Image 1 (cartoon, rainbow, N blue to C red):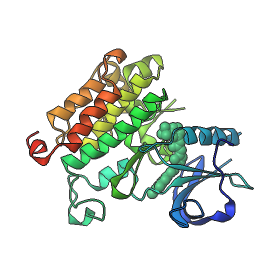
Image 2 (cartoon, rainbow, N blue to C red; image 1 turned 30 degrees about the vertical axis):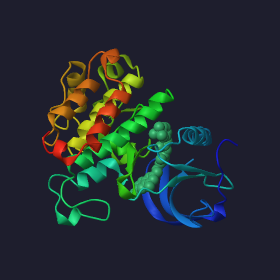
Image 3 (cartoon, helix red, strand yellow; image 1 turned 45 degrees about the vertical axis):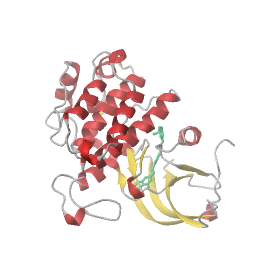
Image 4 (tube, protein in one colour; image 1 turned 120 degrees about the horizontal axis):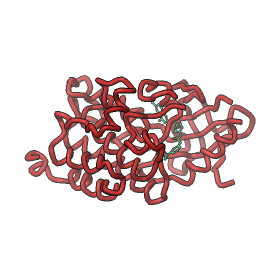
Length: 290
Ligand SMILES: Cc1ccc2nc(CSc3nnc(NC(=O)Nc4cccc(C(F)(F)F)c4)s3)cc(=O)n2c1
C-alpha cells in the first residue's frame, strides 16, 4: 500500500549478478516501469524464504528513504513467489570492488567509459566521498542509524554516481569484514559501539570516517594487519588509522574529526559533507597544492 508494486510479467530475468544467504540478485529487464523508457535494466533481489515480514518491513523502509544518494528502490512483486524487490541497476557494483579495480596499480586497461585509466585522482576520490556524505546527511536528517556503513554497502552507477544501501549479502562476499559472535562490522565501529553496544548518529559519523579511509586507500580493509580481537583492542584503546599515502593532510583532518573518542565531540556529518563537497568542487589549481 505504501510500497509500489510491479507485475511479474513486467520483469524478465536475464542472469544472476550476486548471491547471499538470504537472497539472489538478478539482472532483469523491466517493462512499463518509467515514462522515459518503455524497457530498462534493473536489479532484482529474490528472497530465500518469517522472512516475508523482514522483506515487507525492508520494502516500507526503502520506500521512505528514497533520495539522490540512497539506493533507488522501484518496488516489489508479491504476486506468486518468489517475492521480488526491484532496484536500479548500478553497473560498477559495490564501491569496494570499484575502488580496488582502480587502485594505485591500475593502468590504461582500467580506463573506461565513466572513468579515466590509472588510479582514481584526488578529484574523483573527493567526489565519491562527498556523495556518500550527502547520503549520510539525509539519513541523519531523518534520524535513521545505518549501523553498517562501509564501501561494500555503497553502489556505483553510470557517470560514477554513488549511492548508499545495506546489502544482507555483504555478510557473504565480505565475510572477513565481520566478527561473528550475529555479525559485527568491528573494524568500522567506534569504541562506544564495541564496548557498550550503543549505535547512534555519532557512531555513523565514526563509520563514515572509516569509509573516507577506505576511499583514500583504494578499498583496503581497515586494520588489515590485525586479527579481529587485536582490532577490538586497538579501537577500544584509542589507536587511530594512519593517513593513507593518497590522502592529503586536509582530508586526514576530516577523518580525525570523525574519530573523536567522545561521541558528542565528533563533527556533524553536515559539516563533514560541507568540507568534502567544497574540496570535490574546488578548482584544479587549488587541488594541485593540497
Ligand atoms: C553488479 C551488481 C551487484 C549487485 C547489485 N545489487 C543491487 C541492489 S542489491 C540490494 N539488496 N538489498 C538491498 N536493501 C537495502 O539496501 N536495504 C536497506 C536497509 C536499511 C537501510 C538502507 C539504506 F542504506 F538506504 F539506509 C537500505 S539493496 C543493485 C545493483 O545494481 N547491483 C549490481
